[PDB]
Image 1 (tube, helix red, strand yellow):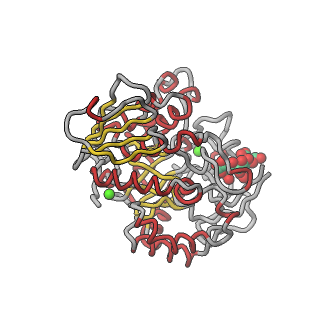
Image 2: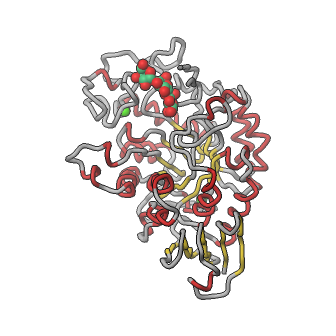
Image 3: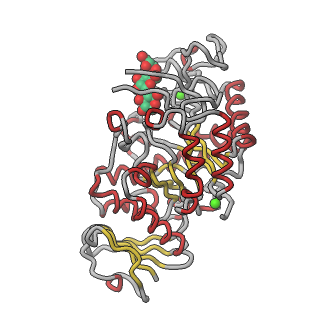
Length: 415
Ligand SMILES: OC[C@H]1O[C@H](O[C@H]2[C@H](O)[C@@H](O)[C@@H](O[C@H]3[C@H](O)[C@@H](O)[C@@H](O)O[C@@H]3CO)O[C@@H]2CO)[C@H](O)[C@@H](O)[C@@H]1O
Ligand SMILES: [Ca+2]
Ligand SMILES: [Ca+2]
């Protein structure tokens, strides 16, 4: 496991991570108060499946409830107490210790933008009129105001002023607490449109400078004002600009947008396919998460932007053979039966030595997506939904078949 920042100082922890999203949306309802126990028991299996890191649910307790129905998942926490719906503080420490002991770095989901301001019994009670809250200042719409230098969550009545020195320091100290007491090897920053990217750089510099980070910026060009250069920019440009300012990797919503809206051939326009290594190496690729994808249980989860089942194998083959840093969704791996396929592709990635900055070339004469990827140990030829017949049509050298699935719709060959 290589540590180390990128040539531009971005915290991609060596560029060699393979991440498991270690939950789905309905965990708090499908395994009440038992998820940490489950992760502890599964730690050795997760490691044996080839993951170097696990993205943990928000560890701050959330007893919210709304009505579709939901609540409790961590994105409306009321304080930092760890005795929440995933399990107790003691069980969290045991799970994090088991995962670390198995070689799996623990990444915590953290939610600085807002909190359950209205919850009756909590340990953090911030009054009005002292600058702690976005709506201490005039709030005319979903854009920065004098108490919140980013966007707001829905109505904004629970957005925190993360730039207030007291609030900044509260989160700084809690990140340090997760590192010292809960085994954190990094963090996933939620809703990063809600606050300044430079504040993520500051928090990481203060409390976890050598750790892995990733931010979730889900905001299309249409959501920016007419006079903002991002209104006419690509999805790639928008997320790359965030990464530059946070010095953090960023979820590849450019790739996700092409997977949802474009053809398979168009998947080459994700951030992770960019020919500039400073661009593609900061991409954190994924197929679905707890928000975009389905989950087992009530209402099938959120499924706000889910990839159809006819493309799931192709999408995992792409992200696991290509540059950027890939994330595997719990439910594909361990609920819905794609685990053996994903296990095989993780082994292919590791055997080939594909890393976040590996070169990737796209080839034009065929249907679907045809790519050659230069790993540190092997070259891969990847053909997805393609009429490519054999790797010698597009690459020099001697190749052996590594993957052949879905009636040849997923094929990978290796040097
Ligand atoms: O009446 C205003 C009050 O209610 C609303 O907040 C609730 C949302 O309506 C509700 O959807 C849910 O939000 C969750 C998201 O659906 C989910 O995708 C994920 O991001 O976690 C969210 C938080 O759990 O819960 C919130 C808060 O209970 C309204 O947005 C606000 O003006 C205010 O909270
Ligand atoms: Ca690493
Ligand atoms: Ca905000």
